[PDB]
Picture (cartoon, rainbow, N blue to C red):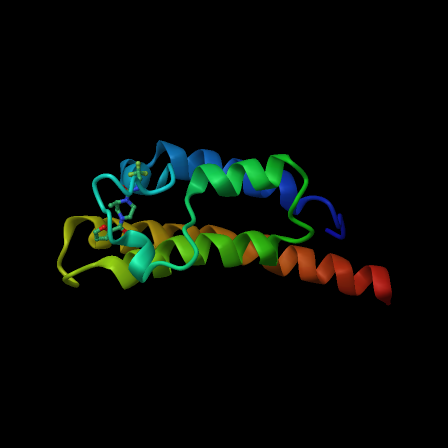
Length: 120
Ligand SMILES: C[C@@H]1CN(C(=O)c2ccco2)CCN1C(=O)NCC(F)(F)F
């Protein structure tokens, strides 16, 4: 399965599944500082799923590794901000992360295999 471009539609589909998850609600838009006025004190690089989707559709990811780095930043920012490991939003981030990692594994493997086949 050596299609070097297949990752992009696979990532669009996975983002659609993440938008249908109730666990994505808090991560679907850039954090509102009005509600969280200290957020940029703690979080140097905000990230959210709408920004990831727009960056993909603009053609501003070269590889699924770059998309994966931005999605992992959504989850690390939620760990950096949580006052507790028990909190609602942090618990939603951990379930959504497990879902994402389960689904991105094959996208990354197929892409890297396709690249190796191209360079053979
Ligand atoms: C505060 C929330 C959740 N959150 C956290 O990581 C977190 C962990 C513990 C407390 O907050 C950051 C993202 N947040 C937003 O408002 N984002 C805008 C939205 F929701 F419209 F997409």
